[PDB]
Length: 248
Length: 248
Image 1 (tube, rainbow over the protein chains, first blue to last red):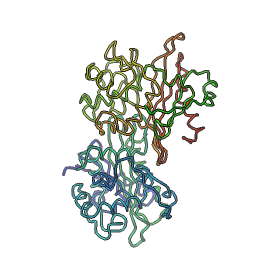
Image 2: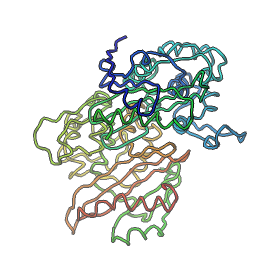
Image 3: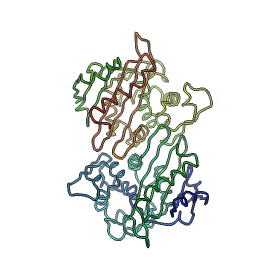
Image 4: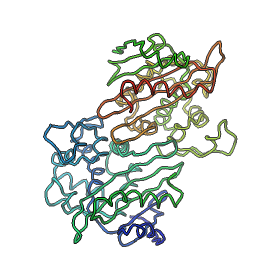
């Protein structure tokens, strides 16, 4: 739509420090004032992984599959991929711990007719849901770029998605990850897998930061072949945001 | 009310440690299950002070005086009574630093007729707004009890006040003071002043805690004639909530 972005290569110097391939997109106030380290990668589409439980939650609510924000998602006892999902969760709880099975059931209930329509309204990436409605965002064909992520989060922050203001606000509170007087972060992690070295997977961090009267939108992704490199999905963008005076 | 409250004197330990006359009220799930150290003080009514910014913020949005959650309250450069207020503030910022002059301007614009009406719909204390539109909650006749605070915070959590749900949600985001994966706190302080020693002022801490799938509502007040006592408005309820295994 609109989107003014400048490449800045001095930023590449924290990716090189740790020998990483990835992209950071940072916007001040609006998508009218963005910067990135790599313009080509910024616009390249990757697997969303867990960053998809932002759009997925909104759709849940729009459709009524999620009753409201107080709904509790009961564990059934049948074990799960990780212990920290073995328990009941609130909507917020499940997003924050990235509880795949809750969202799998959301998606089945929602149904591809609906999922397709909403991803159309949201301009979410390539809008390709195909390859099983259970996992298209984990190992299927849906792809989204960092630029597209920033535009989507800006829409959400402003309540301009095609959804009730109500549902947008619910999902926004579920995303808060840091709360201080005059410093608020909304955030979502993602990690597809170590894939292989032929085809490495992707790690994400997306969100936005309110500081005093300013807002910064951001999106970060990096090639990942080694699960121990995963902390970098935070520390690189953190150091970049620090150098700009932001974090602090 | 369906308010069911049990006095429990064991809690008096954390008060007499510090020679504090005060009251803590704690409810699990709903007002159907509340505990207090002092049943009489629980129902006694005090100046709300800055805890009043919660209803005030909601009424500001409901009346249109506050435009939406992104409104910026501009400092005019003129001296203000605390230095943390001499800056432009968002709605959350104003609330989180208790920026009194921001809310005074809001209130003058809401006017007496609309304020009266909303305090009636919310059942906010004795609903008495006389003796100056821009200071009734600071030094005027308005009074509310801890019990009433808990019943008010509860309706806000459930989105059952006579206000749009979206306005309730906006105000709830502004009150977040602590954010972890499965542990969310919403809270607000207040302090009327040191009063006299004949007739003490009051300090407050009120809010709720979402832990896992449980919610706890709380309200604390104490007599205060000395500013150095002020940290106890947090440290006492904190210790009680830890002994019940809520926080920690």
